[PDB]
Length: 133
Length: 126
Length: 127
Image 1 (cartoon, rainbow over the protein chains, first blue to last red):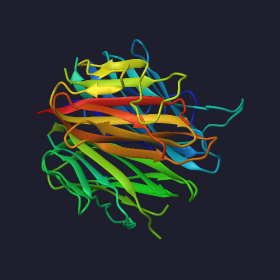
Image 2: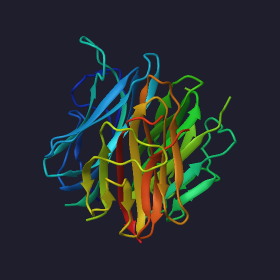
Image 3: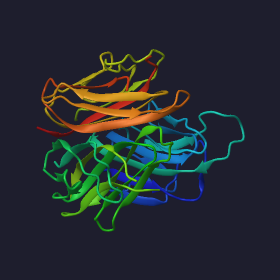
Image 4: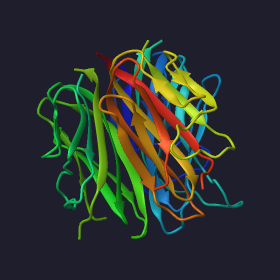
């Protein structure tokens, strides 16, 4: 047994911009490393990890994969499609993490001006240890 | 370790609500996959990673499914115009028992051709 | 420690057709298997590997995962969208590699453009 998780977000609530995506269904979490209420994976086992997400919203969808590791990770994945269209954006990375480092996803508004309302977001976020540091 | 990668690249249409079948096997270390049925069947109980990347012209809805307990049903849809063909990706980390099947199947959220790569491997043994 | 890498292309220059995408930032490379200047992963440890990329470019984007294995891999992933739209295409595979085998991604015309790309890979088991 090693860290391995799969968490799902499927709900009516809008997902706030620039805050960690939270999830309402835990499919797997072997080492109990993920808190679906905060949206954070928190590393207990130091090592190299794989993370990947698959997510959709109506209209433009931008998500960042982020970490509190040093140096920090901030990777953006954006579908700049039309308002009426809903697509699945996927992104992810192989990351080296220390004990206590956090990893999450976060929506942002990749374009447009002030005053945009957050939107519903379907999301599957997956991750697992590749090897122990 | 169980580990596979299978490819659908063909002229036939992919029927709705049936497992996607494949014509090319790139990898199948433990011979867990039958491309003619579209099923991965677990031999080694444990925690697995699964991912697909697929494209069709126009709207494409795919479900990752299992006969594990309780059964998985995860949808991934591109709702785009009929002129546009795009890649939809989806997948999960699943806990499997021996004999559990895992597959992908299209659904309408007139079938079409479907390009698909479906990948999977054991993360750890139970 | 296992072969495991994550490389990032986030720059200005266009990614030419039919040659390996090169990268300007190495996020992870545990076994020093990736050379970002060439765009190649080169296998040192024989075994079964997982490879995956996520990339975006303005308008149409076609990317191909390739290897010099026997037999060689050529797996295409295409987003056939309009000119004013940037989307993320993803693709990948599980591949069996011998020492010296090379793996990479390359753009093709399904007018080159800049390309944001993250390319990841890791050993699943040793052969």
